[PDB]
Each structure stands twice: as C-alpha cells, then as structure tokens.
Length: 277
Image (cartoon, rainbow, N blue to C red; front, side):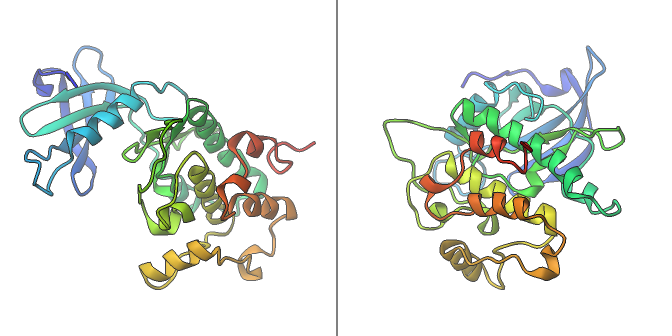
C-alpha cells in the first residue's frame, strides 16, 4: 500500500497511447527532471467490492510488491507508482521494439542457432525469477518484448506480472487461469500450481518459435483445453522437417503432463540444445 499521492502530471509529460486492455492503458511519458522516457500504465481501480469493472487492490498490491523485488536485464523494471481516486499508475521501463515474434516474422529465414540466442534470453529471465521463487504464470509470446529492434543484438524484456505469485512453501496454490493455448494442464484441471507451469509455457513458446504453428490451439476454446489436458500435440513434417532432434527433445522434456517430470529451469539451461557439450 502507501503509493505516491502527487499528481503524475506534475512529474511527467504523457503522450500517445501505446496500447490498451480490459482495465488498462499504457502511454509513453517523459520524466520532467531527467528527460528520460518511460511507459505509464494506468490501471483502473475496482472502487466497490461488488463491481466487476476495475482491478482489486489485493491484485495490484501483489503485482507491485513482486515488481519492486526484481532487478534483471531480461525482466521489465518498475520505476515509480502513483495513485489517484480512480487509477494506480505504474511508471515502467519503456520497451520500443514491440513483440519479439512480430520482429522475427519480418526477417528472412532464421536459423535454429539464431532462434536459440533469443530463447536463451527468455531462459535467463525465467532462471532469475524462479531463483527468487516467483512464478510468472502468464508466459506467452505477446509478453516477450524487445527493448530496441534497431541494434546488433536486440535485448528481450519479460513483461506483465498480473498473475505472478510468490511460491509459498506451506500452502498449495490452485487456479490462475491465463490464456488456454499457453497454460499447463494443472491450470486447466485446477490442480496444485508451482514453478513448473512456466516451464510448460516455455515449451509452447519454443514450439511456436521454431515452427510458427501453435501446438495445442484447436477450433474452439474447449478443444484447446482438451488438447492441453491430454497432451495431444505432434511435430508435423510440414512444420518441422528442418528441425533438429535436439530441439525436439527439448520441447518433449517440457511438454510433460506430470509437473514433477518436467524439466526445471536449471535443467533447461544445461540441455545439449542450449549448451552444446
């Protein structure tokens, strides 16, 4: 609680809408004292407990209190938090390169090698979070952004900590429910949740990175859910004929129903696809 009560317009000049969502908008802003640019996320408060507009204070406080812990090159950094009668305003590091997969869909071929160089940045961000026992719980391609797309080696940033939670050793956590196509089976079946759900999501992300196809997406939401629950996927030759045996082995070891048999983030960093022996 106990966020900054000044008017954000006294400290920042805000400009153009960068994006929006159900209860939020993100605008570019410029800090008056320094001249630096940031992104400003305006989150609408649920102002009455019974209202289904806006975001509960419990959920905003949880997100803010996790973001305040994190400092790593591959995760978004939070700069300040303001609040007025209707909104909580997060001042975040600006990512101007857009979604990683939009950038990649514009290039020529993309070798496996090139692809794993981006993937390794995702791994290193997740390794940090899990090292601090934070589960992101919403890893998906649209939450993988680039700082700047017009440099030699573009740097990725993981964003959106709206479902992130600190793992509590002494209490099981059940339901988070993000987007069907990218959620692990234990999310679909309302089973105990931990760090392993993010390792499943990385598997999905890796499958899409290499192929452009989604492993589990079906024709309705219920069919996608049943594909996930049943681990109904395949490496179809149309999409995977140029993909190494090692790349496929990495995906297989992540897309595992039983969480306790899934590779961990530390295992993933030592796999021979990622660290050739």
